[PDB]
Length: 307
Length: 97
Length: 47
Image (cartoon, rainbow over all chains, first blue to last red):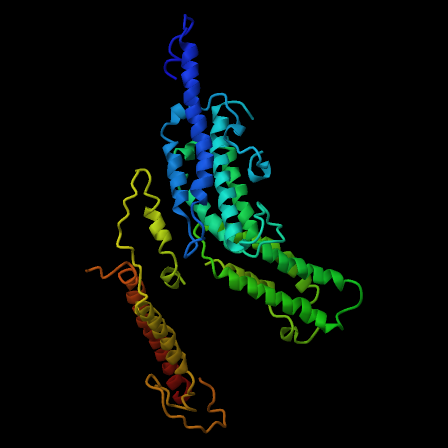
């Protein structure tokens, strides 16, 4: 970088060979970056089981402190981003739905582009490993909160989001912190919202067949079919306390994830029970013996679901 | 909530804290007598034993407001649990209190 | 060792001394309100 910049307007004739063995040291970048992605693939797929208390494989610690070894070569990284594709770190049979990525302009583009693509590779390979290790007879189907296949979307969700807890808690104080501005934050956000929505999935089942249970008996009269009262409201309480029950298995670590999953699933549930509670709270002198919660107290349950 | 949330409650993520190497720098020399393993030989049962201390002390605490005070002035009923004089009728008092 | 402990008894004196604060505070509060209530029972029955 210092020599090809040095002073120009002059004869410079080994400059070609500078670009040729520097073309081989961009095969050291290039090979070090396909090495980075394949490093994620093999070094990740080293492990086989989700941990005892289901934490974070320290191959990811290796991956992120590996990235801070990519950090402090910073200006040589900047020049080292020269004239080279996204597909120069890609196993080409991928899909771009794997990559939360939405230009070709400078090396600051390929900075956040490249590194955040590497953490997307971390996402798809960790995700794949969970998809294997919980249903060991199936196809790993990926990036799918709408999956009709997984039974562990909460569990995989808390696992992966502890891995991302690690990743942004090394981009906490990094130079990557100051490197990967703009989009890559939001790339990390979409990365989160995948597994977040995995932990909203069966809550969307509860709300789903709740308002579907509004829909199928939206035909006739007021509920003289009081099996529909205790169907919707009882089974709503059943699945609600199932979801609160399996919420207890996981105890979050980012406060903003507590705010995130909290306000997400609040915004998922509430207006259904608002118009629906308030629609059907006119059926007994004691609806108490059939319908249990207010939105006040259910809101309070959610607000101390998040200790 | 937190104290139960340290027993199995990771307490390994705390090991993941310095097992982020505190990178930078490069090591990764974590030789903490890890850690607080802990307590599975009955000290966890000492912890839950203390929790039985707490909810037990609340149980005898509000259970002192079971006698009304047995119907009447046993008013300074600060200690202790006895004397089930079962004259249930009437007011003055099943009240407690 | 000591250590005394292994956080989890030093930091579960954050339990133990503070479970002793739940207990000593429990006797404190029940002592307070119970004492004033019985004081409002000689008020409330005798007086």
